[PDB]
Image 1: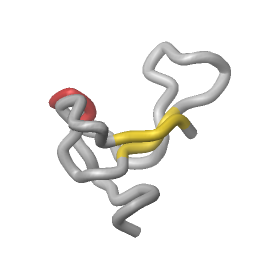
Image 2: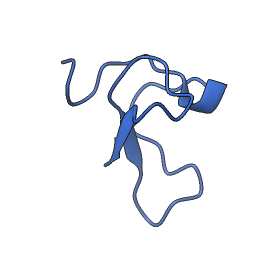
Image 3: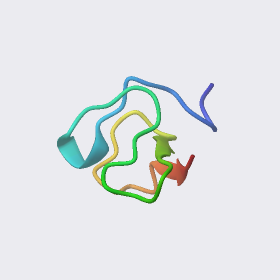
Image 4: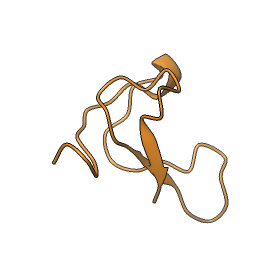
Length: 45
């Protein structure tokens, strides 16, 4: 996929694969573009 979830991706330079709560709320999110760095590279999961 290239508009839903690629992986592996780089959350703000943290690196991740599947979704990730990262301290969210009983859930998590996924990264759209490969590198995240905050470049609208995600969506909540």
